[PDB]
Every structure is written in C-alpha cells, then in structure tokens.
Amino acid sequence: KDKPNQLTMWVDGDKQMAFYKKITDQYTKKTGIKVKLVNIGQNDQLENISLDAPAGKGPDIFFLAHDNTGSAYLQGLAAEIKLSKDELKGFNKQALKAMNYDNKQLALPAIVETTALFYNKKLVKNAPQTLEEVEANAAKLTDSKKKQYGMLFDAKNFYFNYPFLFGNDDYIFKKNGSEYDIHQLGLNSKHVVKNAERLQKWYDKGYLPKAATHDVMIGLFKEGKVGQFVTGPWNINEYQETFGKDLGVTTLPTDGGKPMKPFLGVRGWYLSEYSKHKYWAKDLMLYITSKDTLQKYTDEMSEITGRVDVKSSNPNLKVFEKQARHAEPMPNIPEMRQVWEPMGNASIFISNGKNPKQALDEATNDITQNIKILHP
C-alpha cells in the first residue's frame, strides 16, 4: 500500500477523456499520484490490452462494455476486485452482477443503459401501467389511414423485444446465482412461445408494421404519429425539443405480474492483471466511480450511471434511472454472442407469420450447434 508515482487509465473517447482529466487532476491533488489518460475506444480495449499488457506498457484500469466480462477474465486480462460493503454501497446491485463472472466482481459500473416507454401526451394522456393498457391504446390509436400507430418497438430485434418475450421465470441461459449454464437454454420455453405468439398477434392486428425499422420508428414518433414507443434514451433531447411538455416517459409496465424487465447494458472500469499497483489502481477506480464523480458525470453527459445515489435533474432521465434498477443484464459470457443473430432471425420470421414455436425451436437448435462449434 505504498503509492506509485503514476497510474494509467484507458478512456473511451475524447469527450470522456476531457471529463476524466478534470476528475483525475483532483485525484492527483489529493494523493499526489499522477494519472496518465489514454483515449482508446471500448471496442478496441480488449484487443489492445491483450498485446500491450504483457509488454508492460498497459493501463492499470481500463474500460469495456460488460458483455466482455467473461472474455476479459478468461484471457487473464481482467483481475478480481475485492470490495467492502461500504465500497459497494451506492452501486446498482444489478449492474454489479453484470460485471460479475465466475463469482468474482471484475468491474465497477460507470454507465448503464436500458429502454423505457415514451409516450406522446397528445395521443395517450396517461402513463400506461399494464401491458393490457398499452395494447388497449394500440387498439384505439392504430389507424391504417393516418399512418398512426398506438404502440411501437423494433420487435424484429431481440434486444428490444426481450421484455415482451421474457418474464421472471423465463431465461436465456439457466442462472445458478450470478453464473450461467451454457447447455441449458430457455429461449423456447412454453411461456416464451406463448409471448412470441402474442407478438405475432400484434403484427397480425396491424399494431407493429413489418416494413418499419428502428430508425423509421424514431421518425414516426417525432411526426406525432405514435402513441407509445419503447426505445433507449439516445434521442431524448430531440423528443424534448419536439414535444416539450407533451413528452411522457415511464418505466415498462407490468405483464400479469411484476414490472417488465428490459435488458441492462453496463459499461465500466476493469483492473488489469498486469497492473503493478492494484491497490491504488482500485483506489482510483473508486474515486472515479464515486457519488461525487458520477453525479457530475450525469449532469454533464446526460447518461444514466451505475450508482443508485446519483440523480439527474432531468425528470425524463429520472425514469431511466428507475428502469435501470429493475432490469436484467445481458448475459456477460462469451457464448451470449451466439444468441443475438439466431433470435433476431427468429423474430424476423415471427414478424413474417412463421409458427413461433418452430421459430424459437430453430433458434435454440442453431444456438446450441453454434456454441459447440465456436466454444468447444
């Protein structure tokens, strides 16, 4: 626990690098440890650290999307972070799980992301509480003529249709706590099929258009033609600009049970196994993931963070803060990469009238087969 002269961190982008410079300048004034910052996109940090780490010219702490947690660990790049309860206090419990593999905490969440339900108050006056209300608004507002839709979401994309397909008991890979069994898939369970048949019914009834893509849906919502729209927080400022006080945002509704859980995507800091100063590297991660820091972060970037004690002053983003506390992390294991395309294909097929059970069965067999190939 004897201080180094410098700690190096890899930051994702010029915007964030400017933000963390300010933050780390203060870290230096407090500890007297200089901090070198290096701008390296998160889509390139694993591959780079894979090379630079062994050469001794790697970072102490680096930044990745949580989907990579398993790979970073299996490769011997990401080191376990031992934390106290007081250190964990304040963090989103689920974001932490998203960064927990092989029963080890491997990162601290900085940014979180989920969808939520936007609504145009000129068409839907009250925030829908149940999926039945959402459907009911669909039945009322959807009209061939006006090119108006009661509800929308990119149902061909598994990322967006997940909460509509999977409730509490359902799963992608069977969970044994915070770990996943890769040989036990739940994509074609009685209940997912049943929900998939419901999805098919919405297409049949004209609620979801087969021709539109997520980008088209964004455009239609902005034209004031869409009552309700499940999507991410990415275009929030342009919806505010367009709708002002007529922009409603609420968490996803209940679906016959607990509130629906969308996927949770987390990005945060990992500790290099090749750090020669793990103790202080951690001291730095903790400083940069503090209430004080991430609060300044949310204010200045308009993104939801990995802390439940950080609060956006934007009431629309406050809804996403809540949503982020009731969400399911995208499985953080290498094998998950094999699920996206087949389920996507399944979804496309359902949209086109294919028997949903067959579609989910096909996807399941294909995922099983593909995992056996790329993950012997």
Image (cartoon, rainbow, N blue to C red):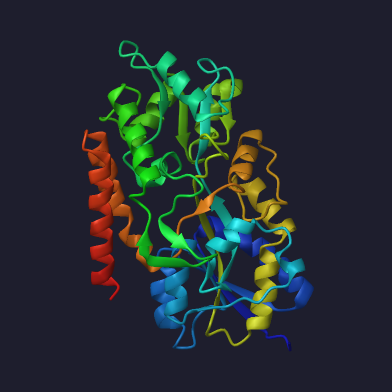
Residue found at the far front of this picture: 190
**Left or right, residue 150 beside residue 178:** left
Rendering coords of residue 305 (x, y %): 62, 52
Residue 163 higher or lower than 375, as above or below: above
Residue positioned 30% across, 49% down in the render: 343
Rendering coords of residue 110 (x, y %): 60, 59
Rendering coords of residue 290 (x, y %): 71, 61
Residue 159 higher or lower than 127, as above or below: below
Rendering coords of residue 42 (x, y %): 45, 63
**Left or right, residue 279 beside residue 123:** right
Residue 93 higher or lower than 347, as above or below: below
The one nearer the camera, 189 or 333, is: 189
Q: Quadrant of residue 97?
A: bottom right
Q: Which quarter of the rendered picture does the C terminus lie within?
A: bottom left
Q: Which quarter of the rendered picture does the N terminus lie within?
A: bottom right
The one nearer the camera, 331 or 186, is: 186
Q: How many marks?
A: 0
Residue positioned 31% across, 35% down in the render: 213
* Residue 150 visible in image: yes
* Residue 17 visible in image: no
The one nearer the camera, 262 or 111, is: 262
Residue positioned 67% across, 59% down in the render: 91
Residue positioned 50% across, 41% down in the render: 115
Residue 264 higher or lower than 127, as above or below: below
The one nearer the camera, 371 or 31, is: 371
